[PDB]
Amino acid sequence: AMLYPILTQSRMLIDLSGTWRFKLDDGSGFEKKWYEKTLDDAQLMPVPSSYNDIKESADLRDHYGWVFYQRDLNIPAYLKTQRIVLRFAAVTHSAKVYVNGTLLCEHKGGFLPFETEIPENLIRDENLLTVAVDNRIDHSTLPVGREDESNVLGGSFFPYTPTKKQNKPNFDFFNYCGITRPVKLYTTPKDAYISDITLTSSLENNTARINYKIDTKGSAHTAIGVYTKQGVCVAQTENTGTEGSLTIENAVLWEPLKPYLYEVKISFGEDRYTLPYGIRSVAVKGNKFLINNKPFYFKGYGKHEDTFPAGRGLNMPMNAKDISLMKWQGANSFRTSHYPYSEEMMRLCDEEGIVVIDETTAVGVHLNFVNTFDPIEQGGIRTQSHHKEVIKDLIARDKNHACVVMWSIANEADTGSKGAYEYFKPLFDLARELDPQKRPCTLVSLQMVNYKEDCTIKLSDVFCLNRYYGWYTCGADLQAAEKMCREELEFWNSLGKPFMYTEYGADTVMGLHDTTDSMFTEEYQVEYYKTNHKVTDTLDCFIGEQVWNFADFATSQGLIRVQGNKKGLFTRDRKPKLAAHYFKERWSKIPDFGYKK
Amino acid sequence: NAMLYPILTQSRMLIDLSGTWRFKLDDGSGFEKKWYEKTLDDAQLMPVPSSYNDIKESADLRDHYGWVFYQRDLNIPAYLKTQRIVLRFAAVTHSAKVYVNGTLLCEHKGGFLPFETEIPENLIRDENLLTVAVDNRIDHSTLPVGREDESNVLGGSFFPYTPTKKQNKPNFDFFNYCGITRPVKLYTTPKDAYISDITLTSSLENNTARINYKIDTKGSAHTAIGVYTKQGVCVAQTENTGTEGSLTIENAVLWEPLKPYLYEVKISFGEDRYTLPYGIRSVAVKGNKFLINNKPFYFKGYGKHEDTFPAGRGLNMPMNAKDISLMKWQGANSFRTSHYPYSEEMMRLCDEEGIVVIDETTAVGVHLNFRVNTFDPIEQGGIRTQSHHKEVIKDLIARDKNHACVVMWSIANEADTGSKGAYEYFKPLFDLARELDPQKRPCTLVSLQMVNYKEDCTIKLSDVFCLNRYYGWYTCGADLQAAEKMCREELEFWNSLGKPFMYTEYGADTVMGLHDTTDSMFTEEYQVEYYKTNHKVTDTLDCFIGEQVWNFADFATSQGLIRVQGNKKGLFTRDRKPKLAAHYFKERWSKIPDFGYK
Ligand SMILES: [Cl-]
Ligand SMILES: [Cl-]
Ligand SMILES: [Cl-]
Ligand SMILES: [Cl-]
């Protein structure tokens, strides 16, 4: 259970972000127990931020292993009358958290929150908070790191021996690590408090019924009230226990680009918590993706959390800039490729009416780009257990978001190979079991020669395809790209279920131009997209287009990465390429609902 | 006036109120209709802290004239009422009205320095609204100055036209970024006895390092002070002490440029607890030398701006750290807070990192003639800024007095200091700065390039002459031989005065990616040749003790025919990428020591 920490009449909220001490592990930090004392001979690092790009050091950017963050934590003893909690919104990839040299918690998974109470007895007059952060990835982590597998995107013409041991990402984006999202101290009443809130809605005529389950610790009485934005109470139930329901007459529905959030206020004993909440329905019916019973057409992007110089770190001005650009362009949606995004972004999307495909950290689950899904004993991928935990934690965090309409279980896994169905079926079953709203589930399909053998066909409610007709195949032959595109997409269209692009694009360096089709130029990016839409616009089961990518982003180094991935419609500093203007024109003429009715 | 930086302590809560706020442009009725009394209706959302101008894609918002309203809910525990509850605004640009529920709590003028107000506990209901109205308007009474009838010298048209809407008329180059620029926080102290200010100075005579302290308090209680090394070893302490005293620091390590050392000075008063980082060092001007720890310093660095995309002037902690890392990579040791006080987070980071700072007021644009003279009597049209200028000096020194990194106060940038009345305007301000700084640091004003440079009143006022000169850009453009000759003729006059002088600005607009082997303005090669030409002169002058370029990085400005999407004089681009000249300076500054160059 991970409610977003907020300031309330029963809950303090103390941000610990700022300038922290920082030290690379030299192989002796745990042996010499650096967490027991002030870090010596240390640097300074902003928190929240990825650490890789803050300095000018390749040894720091390309570090392998642990680093140690630390700050002083001097708090009033009178907080000891309350329950005291340290919340880590995200520490990438793995964390060990120490207060005064006592290990308080550990966490695996770099993109979801975790928390620990501080035992009263540990809090001295002066305290040290130390966070050790591990950046290493392998066959057991999500995202996956290679072990003996070859570098496909960053391969040399002639092999060489690396100077130092390094991570081997099985994914494109740069392995930004550190204290990615805010660290905060918060409090709740000690004896009785709210641990979780679950809300589902049903629309009977113009009356919404909101079913609630309020999970609590301790013995007290539970109450719930639903308020309009302007502050009018529209439903209230007292002494309701855990489960109940209530109704809102003439409810205002949350719609894409037309958001409406009620405020759901909960009391339990002395505890107070307010959750914003939008009322909307999601259903797949035939080849339609229905939001509030209307056939939606996705217009948008796969994104990354990527800005300079914080890397993956929470950047709230850029989040607001990015949503503004989305509305400027006529987009209505994006996918959280390839990890859960910050709660601050997710809550902002609820407020702004941006639809979200919420995706796990499960990218790189692919050992043949020994079978990927062989038994662990025979060398198969070792991620399924953690994959289950990620699904649990992602849905627990994001279940109440109106903006989340579909779960993406994995990106570009080896879904055309033997054992893939056996790996994924329990994960799809888990997502359907745990999501109270029973939203659609998908996996994001890698381009593959044997596409009819993609186990997505047996599992997903929507088929989500990553396809690069005119880039990774048919480059500079867009007539051949159109023919190859049509041949495959007519197969998917024949299945009668909704399908969409979750990735399609062409690397494009701003400022490169040619009137005559030429890879990496701004004009070719436009022609690539025109060619694909010639096909997709004729297919009635094709219900959405999300480009790769919203913006240029950092990646590992190699011969096909021109200082990162250049498939953005915008540059890394959010400037529009020619194709950004193309999509503004195109999306201006396509309705959010009823394009393919 | 006293403004200790808010920190989390054993006696003090610190609750950051930054985040997503509601935001509404005023339409002329916001105060008449009392928008602050209810939830903002039909509002937008805006991140705090940030400038509001670049977050959306709206020219009407970017170029808005007048007021905007920010608002958020403020639901806090009633048990905080056993403490003193304070709302701290680190900066609201330019002027602010702060309401809790329907009640005006405070008003502030001055967009770049903090202000705070206690929240009366009777005002705190079960649910509260916090509304902040923010005014962006500038004129002859604000710092920075807005033009009234004066014409646009950097953005003039060939043919006059009537603007569609009334707009601000900046009398300064940089863009008029406004909004809640820096964090808003709630903090608490004990009610009955608390620390209001701490003043520390250093004494280094007789081979003995001592810290002198003055602790200002409210209420009645006992005072204690201890000084601690980085590793937490107490090196001096006393309990039940006076408000003023001194502590000897045995084995004292001095704060040095690029070799910082900060002690932790821990103070208690009653139940209140506060910790101040502090670097021990001396600053003095003697003859033609700028002495830090009695050694002859050479400034290497930049005039900066607080400018990043998309937050504008807003606090950007990752980029602050990036910028310091780039300065150290380049071999710089210093910068100037052009043209306004910077965030406390930046200043405290400079103390931690060993970056020397020239700390400048908001007084840019004090110039009505770039016929009424700038410093004519107010009643005949002269500039109306002197009263606020005094307040800014008091507030700046009160905020930054304890920083080792601050070695000089800059009283104003490019004022009309060659005109009649300038000395009379500035003498009380130099006197005030010298009276109020407990460390009595050097004072300067930053000198506009002017034909009659020998009449610059800086000569009668300043401890260091700080010159903005553009030999090879705004004069002698594409004639660097003439630039060298003109530069030498004037800088030999300054050298003949025998006092320390330096460049605080010099540079050439440079669009990254434009090149020519043959001297051509706006190319990366010309930027290098411009600097080579200037250094041919400055390296021969024994009283020239510092070079700060204009600018660290490209930054946003008002629109016009000589601003190629902002000011392009950065050594780095706005996204902090090095131009050819940034590599030139890395090589040059690598060969110039911080001490003993001249
Ligand atoms: Cl990627
Ligand atoms: Cl790609
Ligand atoms: Cl400027
Ligand atoms: Cl300039």
Image (spheres, coloured by chain):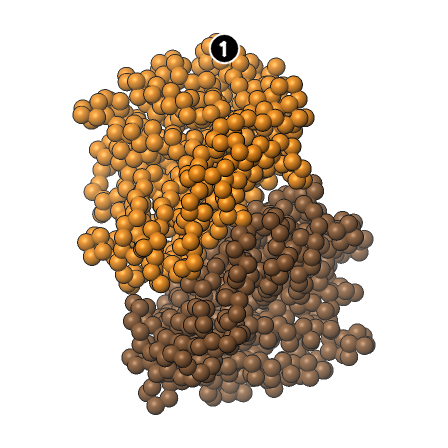
Chain colours: A orange, B brown
**Residue bearing the label numbered 1:** A496
Label 1 chain ID: A
Q: Position of residue A315 (x, y in %)?
A: 49, 47
Q: Residue at x 54, y 22 (%)?
A: A282
The local crowd at label 1, few if under 14, some if 14 to 19, many if 20 or more residues have their Cα within 10 Å, is some
The reply to whether the residue tagged 1 has its Cβ within 8 angstroms of ligand 2 is no
> Horizontal and vertical percent for residue A81?
42, 53
Total labels: the figure holds: 1
What residue lies at 43% left-to-right and 63% top-to-bottom?
A: B9
User: Going by the image, does A69 lie left or right of B459?
Assistant: left
Quadrant of the rendering where the N terminus of chain A is positioned: top left
In front here: B9 or B63?
Answer: B9
Front residue (pair B420, B381): B381
Identity of the residue drawn at 39% across and 73% down: B265
* Kind of residue sitting beneath label 1: Gly
Quarter in which the C terminus of chain A is drawn: top right
Q: Is residue A98 left or right of residue A546?
A: left
Q: Is residue A566 visible?
A: no
Tell me residue A492's x, y (percent): 46, 13
In depth, the one of B523 and A539 nearer the eye is: A539
Where residue A444 sits in the image (x, y, percent)? 41, 24
Element carrying mark 1? loop
Q: Is residue B236 visible?
A: yes
Which sits in the foreground, A70 or A451?
A70
From this view, report whether residue B255 is shown above or below residue A221. below
Depicted B504 relative to depicted A383: above or below: below
